[PDB]
Image (cartoon, coloured by chain):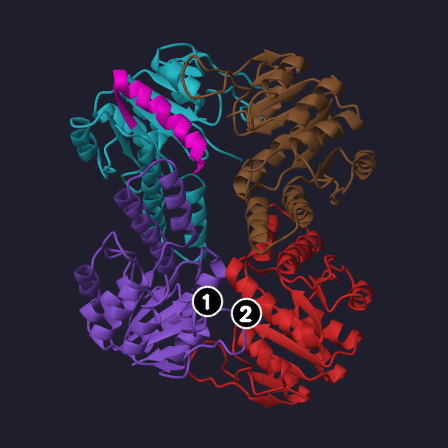
Chain colours: A red, B purple, C brown, D cyan
Amino acid sequence: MKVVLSLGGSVLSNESEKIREFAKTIESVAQQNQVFVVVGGGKLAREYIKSARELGASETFCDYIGIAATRLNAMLLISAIPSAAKKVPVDFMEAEELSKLYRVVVMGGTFPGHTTDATAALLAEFIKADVFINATNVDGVYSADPKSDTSAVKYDRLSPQQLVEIVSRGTNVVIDLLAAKIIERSKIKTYVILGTPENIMKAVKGEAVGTVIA
Amino acid sequence: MKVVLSLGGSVLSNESEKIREFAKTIESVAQQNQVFVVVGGGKLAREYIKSARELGASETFCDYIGIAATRLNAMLLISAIPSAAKKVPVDFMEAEELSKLYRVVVMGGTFPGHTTDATAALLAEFIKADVFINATNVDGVYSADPKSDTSAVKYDRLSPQQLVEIVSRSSGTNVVIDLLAAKIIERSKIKTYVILGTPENIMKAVKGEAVGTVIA
Amino acid sequence: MKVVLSLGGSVLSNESEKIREFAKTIESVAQQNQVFVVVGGGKLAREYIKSARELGASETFCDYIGIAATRLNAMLLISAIPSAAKKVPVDFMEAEELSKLYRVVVMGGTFPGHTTDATAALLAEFIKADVFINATNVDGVYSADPKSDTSAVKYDRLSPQQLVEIVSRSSGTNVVIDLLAAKIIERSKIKTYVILGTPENIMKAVKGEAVGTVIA
Amino acid sequence: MKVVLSLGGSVLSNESEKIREFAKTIESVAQQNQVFVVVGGGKLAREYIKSARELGASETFCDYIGIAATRLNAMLLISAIPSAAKKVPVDFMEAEELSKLYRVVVMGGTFPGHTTDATAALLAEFIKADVFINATNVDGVYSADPKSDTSAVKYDRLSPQQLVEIVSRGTNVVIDLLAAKIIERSKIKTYVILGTPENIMKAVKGEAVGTVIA
């Protein structure tokens, strides 16, 4: 009922119809429940940090650029969902404050550090979330020897401790180590899924999608 | 084992890391098998045709610019995969010729007409492909109309004839696959996939699993 | 000596080297003088507003996204110039406050309304600027209508009142400078330039020379 | 009367109205005379080579990508000019062949090597051009201590030999050394100018713009 959804980089980079698709799902879940959405920087952030590093930015300043970019993507998503707070919170208190007036709150990053997965895990904990749904571009958590290679299946369920070990332990991560550690501390039922309207809906409805962690 | 992969527009528009991610998958599949890749115009083509129309191009000339663009994207992808033919074929005979010396061939468009899905369907048929993997930005083929709800969903498998019917009635999330592509798939009787184009799904589709919409 | 520079949309959309080229010029001007820079939304804003409108945003909310975008471009530019305030000011008081600690201040938009030219004209007036340099993608202010021939040309100098008249009649290559910008320039009586935004021209305009259209 | 025009990188990167502006001028010059146009890679080439290097391309392959990109920009320009050969020549013979049927020929690069200025200088020589107009983003050739800095004026005229010395001897070049050497050999009246419809027209009409070299 208290959902933290995490939309990573790649997972909806500025395509009008796909964004409409995601928002519609989020709106649906919001009719029944209380949704927090953390968007990531996507192409936008990657691009700009790249360019900003190229121009000789401090890592801290890069960090700011990144957050900015997340906030922008977040704005874009908010356009699409009418029940969302039109304000992009800049911290969790703000995010929770807004949760008292709105069924959907949508934020980018906060602290200039580790990102999105970790950020949303922190948020889930902070607000005592019912379910942390981490919508990524892969289907779940995958074996030692992961990736898009041949020696690979996902784990349909996992313990926190298992997940920690698995990421303790290119290209994209996914789930961050600190995110996992945070999930272990928080004892919050997590999903790691292929981020599509259907799967998100399924995860909300407490079913077998991707990798359940509890 | 003979794979035709289709990477459409949107599906990797010039992001260094994402391209590295796609190449690495294609290279993996190429270690075991024989891969053809057909890239589309993406932002680049859309952008350039848009501008070219704005300046008063003939549709035929827009067509050329489009192919141009596809070929450029294709070159970009080839940088990333070391086992690819450094030539971008300009026709299927070339594409097949190159397939005899390389495990990966990557091409843009050919005939100035219907595109990418159809082009790659044609290529599959031409070379008698084992599997046509159509990596799009949606998850599979979708239901009646369609529009976003729970009772609207993808079809986990389909017959060619079914798929034809599905994209024979519209004129609309089913903006992918093309009608002529589907017709071509029906004629060719080649096992097709319609999937969300990610390295994982592509790998899964190669390994003959449940992804998106399987068509056979 | 107090320079307001205006970099509009198009004028440096995220190309690493071109940005390095602009920064280096701004840093040069900053060695001797006091520089304010107002960047615009470019592709980024156009793109995002386009998408945001498509999704059914209020115009006010589009406005915010636009400002957002400008601010992001501005951040990008700041990476490039080491003598700039690492904060992007969100209003002119901030912008002037920061001008007391830094030789270069770089800002996006402020009020959700008319943009960049007007914004920078306002800023010039606010801080009593010595020179407002409006670096656009055209060469100066242009003649009757206008349309491309030899007898249609730029005006090498102008009075404020003249400029007002020139952009008081249209409703169209004179899509730059804004009407309110011109009105503001007239009120402020601040020496303005309207130029093709290149490092050379900017440097020339700073050094008080014949570039584009001088307005005084 | 036989004009080689050189449009570099930056000088018209895909803006519909500015491209219309350039084409209109080129069309005008073509009413009276015989125009060759060499376009460069601009953002497009820079971007793609960047990405292609990033992905581990050979320098030769980069070279091809670059030419491709030039050819594309060239296509775009041709749309805008009706009296142009709809074919983008891939070599000078082709380029001259087409000159026999068309008043405007527009090409990208040819040999995978030094570029645009040099390419167009070569072309001018090859076809015995009347005037090589090199439309750049700076106003002319500038002093020892050039660039957008304070110790700088342009040279309103120059000898070939002078120009060679000057570039013998960031950021953008401009005029290439080999281009200058080629201009010296060819003894072809050259212009180095700020690439705008007006200046191009002026240069064609044999007037004082930028840096004349003869």
Q: What's the distance in space between the residues labelled 2 and 1, CA to CA?
A: 9 Å
Confirm whether residue D74 shows in the render. yes
- Drawn side of residue B191 relative to residue C81, left or right: left
Instruction: Assign the N terminus of chain A to one quadrant of the image.
Output: bottom right
Q: Nearer the viewer, residue C32 or A142?
A: A142
Specify the amino acid type for callout 2.
Asn
**Residue displayed at 55% across by 83% down:** A210
Horizontal arrangement in the rendering, residue A192 relative to residue B129 (left or right): right
Label 2, residues with CA under 10 Å away: few <14, some 14-19, many ≥20: some
Q: Mostly what secondary structure, the magenta segment?
A: helix
Query: Which quadrant would residue C105 be assigned to in this image?
Result: top right
Q: Which residues are magenta?
A: D12-36
Tell me where residue A71 appears, x and y as whole percent. 68, 57
Residue ID for mark 2: A172
Residue at image x 76%, y 59%?
Answer: A90
Q: Is residue B30 visible?
A: no
C183 with respect to D68 (left or right):
right
Give the structural element (helix, strand or loop) at label 2: loop
Contact, mark 2 vs mark 1 (Cβ under 8 Å):
yes
| Residue type beneath disc 1 | Glu
